[PDB]
Image (cartoon, coloured by chain):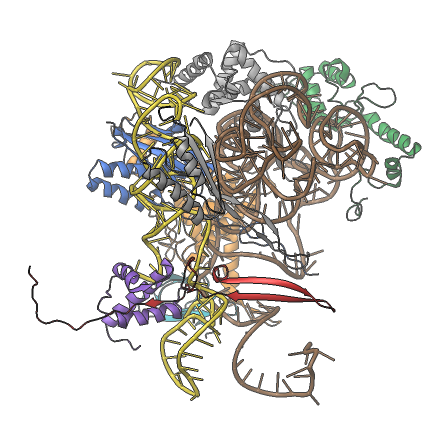
Chain colours: A green, B cyan, C purple, E red, G orange, H blue, I brown, J yellow
Amino acid sequence: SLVVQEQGSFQHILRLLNTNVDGNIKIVYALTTIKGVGRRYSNLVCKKADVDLHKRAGELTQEELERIVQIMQNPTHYKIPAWFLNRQNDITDGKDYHTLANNVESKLRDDLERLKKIRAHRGIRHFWGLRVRGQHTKTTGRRRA
Amino acid sequence: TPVTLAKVIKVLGRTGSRGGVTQVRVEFLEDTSRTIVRNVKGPVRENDILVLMESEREARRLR
Amino acid sequence: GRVRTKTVKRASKALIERYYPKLTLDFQTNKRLCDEIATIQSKRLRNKIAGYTTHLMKRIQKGPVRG
Amino acid sequence: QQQQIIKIRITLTSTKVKQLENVSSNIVKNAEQHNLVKKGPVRLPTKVLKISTRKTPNGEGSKTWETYEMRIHKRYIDLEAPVQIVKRITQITIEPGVDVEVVVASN
Amino acid sequence: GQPVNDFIDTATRHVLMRQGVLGIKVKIMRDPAKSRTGPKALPDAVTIIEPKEEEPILAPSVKDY
Amino acid sequence: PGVSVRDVAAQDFINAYASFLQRQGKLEVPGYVDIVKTSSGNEMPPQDAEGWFYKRAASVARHIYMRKQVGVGKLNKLYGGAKSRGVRPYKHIDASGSINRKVLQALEKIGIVEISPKGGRRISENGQRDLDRIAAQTLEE
Amino acid sequence: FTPVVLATPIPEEVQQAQTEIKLFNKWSFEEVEVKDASLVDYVQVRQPIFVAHTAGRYANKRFRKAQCPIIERLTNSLMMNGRNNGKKLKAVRIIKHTLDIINVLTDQNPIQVVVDAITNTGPREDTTRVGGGGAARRQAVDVSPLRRVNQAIALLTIGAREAAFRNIKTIAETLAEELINAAKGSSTSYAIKKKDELERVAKSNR
Amino acid sequence: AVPSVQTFGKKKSATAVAHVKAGKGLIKVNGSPITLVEPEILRFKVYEPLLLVGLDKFSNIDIRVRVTGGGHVSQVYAIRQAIAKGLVAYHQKYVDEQSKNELKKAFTSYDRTLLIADSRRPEPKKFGGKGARSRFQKSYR
RNA sequence: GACGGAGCCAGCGAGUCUAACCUUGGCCGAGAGGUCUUGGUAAUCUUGUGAAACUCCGUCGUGCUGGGGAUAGAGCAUUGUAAUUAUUGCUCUUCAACGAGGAAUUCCUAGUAAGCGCAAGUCAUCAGCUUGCGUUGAUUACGUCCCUGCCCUUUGUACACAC
RNA sequence: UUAAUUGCGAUAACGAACGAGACCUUAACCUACUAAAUAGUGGUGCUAGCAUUUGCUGGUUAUCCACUUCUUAGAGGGACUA
């Protein structure tokens, strides 16, 4: 039983890669709020950092927080099997990367201009604002698209 | 206490636009000489017991 | 409902005067004798005729029934 | 040489119960008048053959799927007898609508 | 009912005349009493035998031999 | 008298046998664990990333015991589940074969099961040694 | 009592039930009765039962649900969501927990409390619509006892249903709170207040 | 030799086969005792026929039960149905009907379904509606 | 309620030698799938189709939240010559509206609706469809013609293409 | 009165026919008939294991025998409102 009796060292709402993450919620699920990081990329970083799974976000110490940030930046260095990543085997430089909060939207624009620069059909659909994955546009896509 | 106890002595038959109400003849419990036709909603049998708030309003809309 | 058709009533009628003394209040024996005294294609219909003629046998036992 | 045993098995397939048990009874009574020991005629599961289709040649109207369901009935009979009389039992005891296959076995 | 299969046989033909096609639907009921297959009596039909009743005898006796 | 693993609770047996396996420390955990969601239709490896493999080992041990012999496919089908296919209705999807094969291959060396020349994996005398003993211990805990 | 020893080990908490039939081996049908006239022998409690799941046939005859034990019908009435079709055994799990709650609440058998709640939340009289024109009217007369008990159990379960929605409150304690309040009389529960309101509407639109 | 009668019980599709022989009181379901019958809220329901007439007679009779088909609660009723049937069968074959009729009276008086199978059976489903009765949603314009 | 672990019970099918069908078991593989072999022309081999709801235990704890999976991004596979105007499945990344619903309206009285899954038609691949099969399994009423239709008797009619 | 032009009964109508029904198929009953390695069960029966006062399992017609209650499916029987 993790019956905790601590002092007033709890650390509240925090910033990791300049993203607001609550300190009250458990670390594993609270860390999905950084953009480009989802449920499983947040669970595996915790277990690989060997940090405490059954603990909130205000009880984990600063050093392990920085090492978690380090692991998130470096998936190539912590036995992440390269199929667990977001940017699997990219197009330009061929390296296996993972895109983060300040860059998920950057790459979201990036693939967009490259597609609309090659004048691809998916790119022009992105440009016009329609769907891209070849769905049925006749009945749906009315209230926000 | 404005409560009266009565017992079914005869089921008469179903009335109402939806047929969901039934005419029944009922005689009190606290005395065995006051018997009145009244109406009931749900399923009914003989000798059922009825708690009447006002035991005076004779049945309306008979058939 | 289970109302009996004219066929079963007709068969029971034609059955009762033809074989009245042999018929009895007992449905089981009556259903059995329905084999020798007549031919009914289905056991169900034979049971139907037997069931009707049992009731007619009883009713004749208590008072004459016109028809 | 001394009345070699075969352990023969016969399969009888048909859809019609009356004809299937007609030929089955013919075979069984021939075995009985040969005074033979065997396993009784095993009746296979009632093989219903269920298929559902529209009734409408067009698509207009109420949707009427209705099914043509078959009843394949099979019986297999074990027998232990010489060739000389299993050839008799295969040349006879047949009729249209039933197909009989005779197979040697060690069962 | 199945008496349709038991006793009716049907046959439909298309007949090509100069103007078009005529439909011919011949439906035939054979006599159930005839033929030697299946039932000879309709499900509704009821057949009653003649009882051959006799006069009551009022002289009980024995045939001995 | 006779105390084999059918008079003891199945869930408690699996838990206790997993604890016994953890203490004994002869389970050769394959290492890549905590990356497989244990179900190809699931969305995450278990919450007990430090003992769920041992739970799987104990459960498979009981499964092979209660059956004659079981193959990897009948491990997958039983250890699968209803995948939430998203905007479509649920469908049952076969789980990951990797955990099933590795847990069986693990039990091959301890001796709980063997290759079952007739079929897949079947109980062995060595497995009968420890499983019913665990049942007896848990009965008179 | 010198319990019998069997080659199959049966716990003493099952052996002791041999003396008298005990609902869930904790709640007894002795010293329990329907205190409400007009609902006696309709809120069926006399006959014995141990669990509230029975593979019965009560939709066969007009008044064969009347003899059904009330716990079964009430538990069945917990099965009411649109997503909770089926799960009758989940319903009996919930009733088990809520009966345990009620026993601690009242220094008394919980089934007496639930019987009181049914009797007190069964609306005695209400109205039916009469008049097919624009100016329709609500004509109010008394209610048959079986209709009363069915409304009572439905309203109890509906109060639990509304309270259990979108809150941290456990359904077991919600139902227990609702039942105990309906029995004792507090008007802080949904069923008793709606019973009051329906009867009052009938009292006024006579 | 060993006096053994056989009975069975039946729900919609769960079928239970039981052997009732003169013995020590071994009650099992597919090899597990009556005290480990799943689930716990329904275990006492199969316990019912045992408690209805007291364990003294079962001290002389051991029943072996195997269940195939159906669903979990369908079994849960099927075993108890079969147990009542096997008890009355044995105590008809070997024990006086002065006790046997009291047994059958008690069982059916408690619930008629202990020794009578409820003939409530599913009926086929008709085109135009998911369930046997209900049809699809209707449209107008 | 979701998540995770564990317990873990069917039926109705179908399936290739007039050929590439159904595939067990073992191996590779996070998965998707690939692989060697086995069995089956079929109550036998898939298959006790170990299916899911359900059950137990634990996490979450009123936060549109861990519900939800919409749109979109990247990669891995199978079928097809061919997947682009994403076949489909799989991996990860995103968690949008949606706090249960206005008029209106659909279907339904017992193994019933509804929850749950499976099979099959489709088919080279595609099942949110559908036929069946089952698993769990209600409430309410045993009625009335008020609403909607249909039918009958009478009635009225200048209609009969028939209001 | 019936689900029913289903019947009772009243009758210028009588006797009829088709439809309904009757028919058949499916589902539940049958410790009764017939059986069975393509279905199962019992055998301190064969062999072996388990835990040890003996209970649970694996190869058991091909390692045997006895059977059909569960399974199957033929013939029937069963309710016809008794």
In this orientation, which residue lies closer to the viewer: G77 or F113? F113
**x and y, in percent, of residue A58 in the image:** 69, 22
- I117 in relation to A107, above or below: below
Q: Is residue I154 depicted above or below D33 in this figure? A: below
Please indicate whether residue H30 sits to the left or right of residue J32 in the image.
right
Q: Position of residue A139 (x, y in %)?
A: 77, 49
Task: Locate residue C1, reporting x and y percent.
Answer: 42, 64
Quadrant holding the C terminus of chain F: top left
**Image side of residue H138 versus residue F67, left or right:** right
Snapshot quadrant of residue F132: top left
**Which quadrant of the structure image shows residue A134?**
top right
The reply to whether residue H74 is visible in this rendering is: yes
Q: Is residue H37 visible?
A: no
Residue depicted at x 61% and y 51%: D53
Picture quadrant of residue G16: top left
Residue F122 drawn above or below residue A122: above
